Image (spheres, coloured by chain):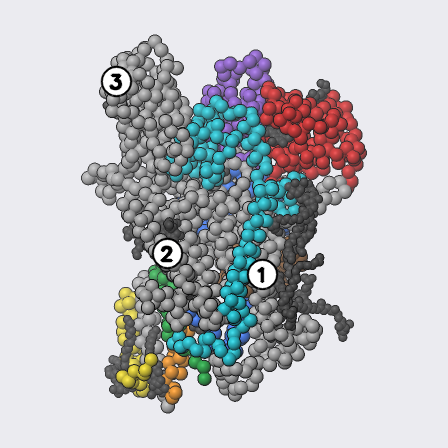
Chain colours: A green, C red, E yellow, G cyan, I orange, J brown, K blue, M purple
Amino acid sequence: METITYVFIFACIIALFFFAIFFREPPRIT
Amino acid sequence: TLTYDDIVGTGLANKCPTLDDTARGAYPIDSSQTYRIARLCLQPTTFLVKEEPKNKRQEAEFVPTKLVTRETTSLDQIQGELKVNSDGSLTFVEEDGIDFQPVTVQMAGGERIPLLFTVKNLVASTQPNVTSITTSTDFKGEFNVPSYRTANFLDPKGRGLASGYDSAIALPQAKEEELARANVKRFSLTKGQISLNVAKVDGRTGEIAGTFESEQLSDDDMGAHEPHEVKIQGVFYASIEPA
Amino acid sequence: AELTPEVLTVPLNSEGKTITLTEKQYLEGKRLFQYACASCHVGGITKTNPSLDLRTETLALATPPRDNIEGLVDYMKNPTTYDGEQEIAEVHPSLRSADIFPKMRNLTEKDLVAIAGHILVEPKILGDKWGGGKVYY
Amino acid sequence: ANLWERFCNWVTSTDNRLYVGWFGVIMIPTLLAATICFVIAFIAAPPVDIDGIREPVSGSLLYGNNIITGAVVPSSNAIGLHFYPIWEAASLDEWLYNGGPYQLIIFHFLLGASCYMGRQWELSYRLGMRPWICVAYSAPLASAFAVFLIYPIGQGSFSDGMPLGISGTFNFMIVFQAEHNILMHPFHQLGVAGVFGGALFCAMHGSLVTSSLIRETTETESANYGYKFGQEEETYNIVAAHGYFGRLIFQYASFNNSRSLHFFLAAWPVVGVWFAALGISTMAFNLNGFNFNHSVIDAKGNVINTWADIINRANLGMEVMHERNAHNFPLDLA
Amino acid sequence: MEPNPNRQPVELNRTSLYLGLLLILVLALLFSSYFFN
Amino acid sequence: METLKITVYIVVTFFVLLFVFGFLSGDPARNPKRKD
Amino acid sequence: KLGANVGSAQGPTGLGKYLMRSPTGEIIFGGETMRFWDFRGPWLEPLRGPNGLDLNKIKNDIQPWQERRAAEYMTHAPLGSLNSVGGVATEINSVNFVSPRSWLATSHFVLAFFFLVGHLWHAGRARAAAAGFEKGIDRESEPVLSMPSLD
Amino acid sequence: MEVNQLGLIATALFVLVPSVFLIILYVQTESQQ
Amino acid sequence: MEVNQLGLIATALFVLVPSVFLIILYVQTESQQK
Amino acid sequence: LIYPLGQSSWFFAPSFGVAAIFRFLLFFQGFHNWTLNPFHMMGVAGVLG
Amino acid sequence: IFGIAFSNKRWLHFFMLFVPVTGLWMSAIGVVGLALNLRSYDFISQEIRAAEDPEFETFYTKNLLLNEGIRAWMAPQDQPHENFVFPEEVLPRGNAL
Amino acid sequence: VRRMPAFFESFPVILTDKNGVVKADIPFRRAESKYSFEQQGVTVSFYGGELNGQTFTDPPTVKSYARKAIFGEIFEFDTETLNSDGIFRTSPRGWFTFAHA
Amino acid sequence: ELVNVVDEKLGTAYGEKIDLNNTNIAAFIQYRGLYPTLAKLIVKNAPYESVEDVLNIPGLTERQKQILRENLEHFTVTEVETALVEGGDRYNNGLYK
Ligand code: CLA
Ligand SMILES: CC(C)=CCC/C(C)=C/CC/C(C)=C/CC/C(C)=C/CC/C(C)=C/CC/C(C)=C/CC/C(C)=C/CC/C(C)=C/CC/C(C)=C/CC1=CC(=O)C(C)=C(C)C1=O
Ligand SMILES: CCCCCCCCCCCCCCCC(=O)OC[C@H](CO[C@@H]1O[C@H](CS(=O)(=O)O)[C@@H](O)[C@H](O)[C@H]1O)OC(=O)CCCCCCCCCCCCCCC
Ligand SMILES: CCCCCCCCCCCCCCCC(=O)OC[C@H](COP(=O)(O)OC[C@@H](O)CO)OC(=O)CCCCCCCCCCCCCCC
Ligand SMILES: CCCCCCCCCCCCCCCC(=O)OC[C@H](COP(=O)(O)OC[C@@H](O)CO)OC(=O)CCCCCCCCCCCCCCC
Ligand code: HEC
Ligand SMILES: CCCCCCCCCCCCO[C@@H]1O[C@H](CO)[C@@H](O[C@H]2O[C@H](CO)[C@@H](O)[C@H](O)[C@H]2O)[C@H](O)[C@H]1O
Ligand SMILES: CCCCCCCS[C@@H]1O[C@H](CO)[C@@H](O)[C@H](O)[C@H]1O
Ligand SMILES: CCCCCCCS[C@@H]1O[C@H](CO)[C@@H](O)[C@H](O)[C@H]1O
Ligand code: OEX
Ligand SMILES: [Ca+2]
Ligand SMILES: [Ca+2]
Ligand SMILES: [Cl-]
Ligand SMILES: [Cl-]
């Protein structure tokens, strides 16, 4: 159970990196 | 005829010397002379470990294992007296040499089995009436297997036999009876058995070679757990000389 | 506390004749001990053989006794094992082996007396620290 | 256009979401290999005989670690500086016992990070920027080289490289103090002034700019909406910022040249961290911290301890305990 | 990217929130004994 | 292990050749300003 | 010399206390120095044979010059402090020693490192200057403003 | 009582996961024009 | 490993409660008339 | 202030000096295992960050 | 280069304040615990396993041995008011050193 | 028995006579031990409490009580009811102080 | 069944005198004339059924036997303990200063 927990949190962080980079709010000059 | 630099890093330094297929002669034993083994070498080619099945009934078998400690396993530069006995048998009495190697092997599924592969204090004798050592000669003997770790060795919590803590200091108010086997270190000393089957003899040089099989217990981690039974098979080399 | 004539008075021989070293003598001894000896005997231990130290009680039980100037000077000319049985100049710095231990080449009798005097005075100052090793640092 | 020319155009393209580039061609596969092996080893690797004494140390989660205690453990002391790729092992089991993952990880990581630094040069050139961001990154890069490569080289073993784990890092630090008295080394002292100073100037600069933002928003809005990405005008009043800081200390202690200011922010932590890296890299060849042990002596010759001597007592504890089964002879000489 | 014309807003009115929370909380009250067993 | 060794050697050589021929392919001219 | 049989002496870990095997089988010295078995020097090679260190030569053939050299080299290991106190970091003051090898390796690492940084600094600058943007971005002609958005 | 030790986490997520799904949907409905 | 039997629920709620708070806020910001 | 006030006396506060401060670090390693502390680790992240 | 970038200069500068300021504040909270010896000294699961299993070792158990060395070797000179006398034979030490 | 100060997670076992002179200890390295309970014939006798009037001479037993004496007076504990792990915790005095500081 | 055999040994004459059958060789330095020459012979020729059998080592000189007699009062013998004599430990037991 602990190992699952640590790996789960880690996996979520990598998922977050993907969305933060590729699905970022795009920078727009206005 | 090779130098260190020819050999360094090839793996050849862990191999015992061999004899040509033509070495099927006979090395005369002069009952009047004194003799020595000036060099005994033992090179394991297989480590087998006896499985421990759940019900004693069904004989447990020795199964093959994977060596994880590399080419560091051979015994060599071993010497000692080669006695001629009343009945013409010979008795090798090991005096000294590189007569032990720690070895770790791994069972199918990953369990590691450290052992002190050794012939320490070997006394091994042939059949009676060995007027000449030939490819019919055999040696059968017993040897001692001291604890894999020696008395100073400290566990990862600092506990030891001749040094170290004598309790689980990280559990200051734990009851101590349940940790006695881990807390009180013990030093094993057991017997192993070996047979050396002579397959080649150079009657001129006094060199012999063959195969061996030894049986001995593995590491018990200074009494923490039960040891396993190990069978080591390999090849050997010995050079005999008038002493 | 001071480095007094009293502190500086040490056995010259086994009969209990003493010599009072001068301060210059003490300081020359320290300096020469560093020059010739401290690479193995820093602080009174012996790095290449930790079983034998330079504590005065240890020197006293050496054969011949080494707990005096003359014993130490003799050691520096012709060193022996602790029981006196083997001469060890081939592997230990001495006047007799100055050919192979060149830092011994220019040492005078007065220099050896000085090194000997340092060895006997240091424990009177440092106590169990002298020959004690890292436990006493 | 040629097939090769189209590919070169794509590799060096300014319009890829992540820049690739020629350094990128080496960086991408090496970092991916290091990362994949790191994650699998941190989860599932069996214990590793780091000190070559058949005493294997468990680093992985599945073998009883948590995030804090887990590590990819350094390769065996028996290996030393020998190159130990997977194919030099008889089996993966042997490779795992002996700490093969650590070598594969560190060597790919150091190559991939060196190429990261080149890539920062490369993109700056493609974009018409000035070229020295890569020079600032050379400070942490040099420090990673110091702990994973230069230190092992000096000491003769990758078993003495920094472990890839949180508690293992602390182990490395404590043993280093015992063996080098690094706290007493002026390059580590410069490192500290670099990172404490870096943090102080970071907070300072942030607070000074934030203090002087021009009012562009109402009370119910985040002030951050008062700046639009790419606007021409500066978003704060540097004269007001300077007027505050100049009076806080005295006028001449304050920067009103933003270029000098930003140069200083770069240079202070970068130079300090170069010196930290050079501390580890020269303690690698055992030129160690200042040793004032028994430096102070009274009229008689009694040692009068100083705080240096108390440090020495703590260092002794670390020294005598570390790798408690590894030393047979009285001096730890590497 | 050109906008996707298939996108639609989603809604959950307050009554639906309350009905839904009641379903979940009562299901939990019913199943929790079996989960603890 | 031999097959693994050859595979990695091929892989590494492939990428290293990309890097070298890549940077030989008119790299100074791949900037937004002066191209000679 | 005291009587130890050095070839058969098992140390605390199970490995030989004085002598063990390298990973390819050569006989080498034991303890932490197992990492240094590639070392070769004239005081030691007389003890080495085709198998590595030769137990017979060790037993019978070590000369006093070899003993002297080993003692000298053990006690001049290249460890010492910045103020030239020779020995491990916990050593007391007494011996004024830092090996020339430590001096020369440390100095040249430091110099070689700053020279890599000088390389990057000047190589980057020479590219920027040859291309005409080493003084900054042309406001009237900012290259990124003419590139498509990343997203 | 010797209950199943996963009972607590099973119960807690059984409640929280769908409750929070609903809350998310409700709140963004309220915030629509 | 004999870990604390509340460590799982504590970690889960530690993650879930604040993450859900942020998700609620983000989605209702997106759904506001743009 | 707080730290020595929880301990036996001011003796255990940091002394004001370079080596004295290094001693204080090493005391905290040996007695408090302070590097294991997640509050220290967040401090590290802030300073290095 | 890195996948993300600042786009808002005000946020950039506020974050420069936030990061080191928050870090120092967290370190202070830890020290307030240490005032009471309320340490993160141990992981209990590690110690239960290690006590029962003398082949289990991690970097965490390795560091505790170093700490035990530090306390025994440093305490007599560092805490003179305790008048500690630790006979040579009680000092924790590994082999040889 | 020399008592454990609060600072120490672990502490050696050292016994001194009434003038503070060391008379016995539990050695870590044994090869140069001079003060072992075995060399010094240390025994323990209890007065008051459950063990009143009892005397122990078996050195492992005497050493076990000496390890307890570093904590002060010696108690019998039920470690089963709560599956107690043997590692000290603070009281509400400690928790209150921490949270409020 | 679980006793530490080294601590037990400390409760025998091994804890009081030099045990000719078990004690590490450096102990012979405590008395005049025993180290290294007689020390080596004594360890090499162990075990001894009684202390006085030490006088019978082959090849001792007449002066050696006399030095031995002078030091019998500092010697003992106890049963050989495997833990103390394996590993070459009588010649180097991992302790230096
Ligand atoms: C990666 C390495 C690393 C890093 C980056 C840090 C970072 C930090 N450590 Mg940790 N430490 C480490 C490794 C590290 N540590 C290790 C391995 C140990 C062994 C356990 C420790 C032991 C340790 C201890 C024991 C302490 C820290 C503390 C700290 C914090 C100090 C913050 C500060 O600036 O105080 C500097 C002081 C201040 C900011 C106070 C105000 C200073 C005023 C403004 C000075 C004014 C001076 C004035 C102008 C006059 C100057 C005169 C001049 C002549 C000198 C910071 C989070 C401290 C902490 O947590 O504090 C809560 C602390 O007590 N560390
Ligand atoms: C009871 C009685 C007697 C009462 C009497 C009281 C009384 C009236 C006294 C008056 C008499 C009197 C004045 C006596 C003086 C006594 C005295 C000397 C007291 C001691 C005071 C003392 C030691 C003060 C310490 C001062 C000190 C250390 C100041 C800091 C200096 C320092 C190291 C600064 C860092 C160096 C430096 C160049 C930093 C710049 C980096 C930085 C912050 C960048 C960020 C930044 C900067 C900008 O600039 C702007 C723009 C922006 C954007 C920005 O990011
Ligand atoms: C024994 C005696 C011999 C001593 C010799 C010692 C040798 C050491 C070499 C030191 C001399 C080098 C000086 C270079 C100056 C410089 O950088 O100019 C570049 C700019 C120009 O200044 C700017 O000057 C500008 C004009 S111009 O560029 O100079 O033309 C002007 O526009 C601007 O307003 C003004 O701020 O300087 C600045 O930006 C001012 C910042 C303050 C100093 C920054 C440099 C050092 C920081 C690193 C410290 C690291 C150590 C800490 C470790 C943690
Ligand atoms: C593995 C990962 C899994 C993650 C999945 C998590 C998501 C699960 C969400 C499911 C919850 C949905 C509940 C919707 C609740 C809800 O929205 O109801 C009201 C809703 C009315 O919908 P309308 O068509 O009126 O549309 C209004 C819209 O605003 C709704 O979006 O009707 C239904 O959804 C029909 C079916 C449910 C009818 C349930 C009523 C139950 C009555 C009370 C029962 C308990 C008491 C019993 C006493 C004995
Ligand atoms: C070749 C590719 C190499 C790198 C690839 C992977 C890099 C991943 C980068 C971080 C992505 C996540 C960002 C989320 C957050 C996010 O999307 O930020 C995006 C945000 C955008 O900034 P703006 O200025 O545009 O923000 C506008 C503000 O006004 C909003 O109010 O960037 C920052 O705030 C920069 C500072 C945060 C930097 C955090 C760095 C984190 C490093 C990693 C730490 C965790 C390690 C755990 C390991 C287990
Ligand atoms: C290392 C190479 C050494 C140097 C330099 C010096 N000595 Fe030494 N010393 C060394 C060893 C290995 C031994 C033991 C030798 C043996 O087999 O017995 C010694 C011994 C001594 C002694 C005897 C100590 C005792 O308790 O009996 C003395 C008095 C002594 N050494 C003095 C001495 C002096 C004065 C030196 C400098 C001139 C010196 N030694 C250098 C190793 C080394
Ligand atoms: C741990 C358990 C977690 C469960 C998590 C569940 C995730 C729930 C995701 C629901 C997302 C709803 O998605 C959201 O829909 C709304 C409308 O409803 C969209 O909103 C769009 O339409 C609305 C309404 O006409 C306009 O005012 C708005 O300007 C427009 O953007 C949002 O742009 C979108 O972000
Ligand atoms: C993506 C999967 C990679 C992880 C593979 C883990 C190694 S394989 C793993 O090894 C263990 C010990 O050898 C065995 O006990 C176990 O049964 C086996 O599944
Ligand atoms: C039978 C053991 C030998 C006698 C010495 C026991 C010390 S006293 C002993 O201490 C324990 C903690 O270790 C308590 O849990 C227990 O209640 C108590 O009986
Ligand atoms: O391996 Mn890691 O650590 Ca560098 O010192 Mn030597 O070796 Mn080991 O001991 Mn101390
Ligand atoms: Ca046959
Ligand atoms: Ca229990
Ligand atoms: Cl360690
Ligand atoms: Cl060693």
Residue C5 numbered mark, or none = none
- Can residue D51 be seen by looking at this rendering? no
Chain hosting mark 1: D
Q: Kindly identify the amino acid type of the residue bearing the numbered disc 3.
A: Gly
Which residue: 78% across, 27% down? C19
In the rendered image, which residue does mark 2 sit on?
A: F17
Up the image or down, E22 lies above or below L80; here it is: below
Dot 2 falls on a residue whose secondary structure is helix
Taking the image in four quarters, ligand 1 sits in the one at: bottom right
Which residue: 65% across, 37% down? C43
In the rendered image, which residue does mark 3 sit on?
A: B25
In the rendered image, which residue does mark 1 sit on?
A: D271
Which image quadrant is residue K43 in?
bottom left
Which residue: 40% across, 35% down? B8
Chain hosting mark 3: B
Specify the quadrant that holds the N terminus of chain E.
Answer: bottom left
Dot 1 falls on a residue whose secondary structure is helix
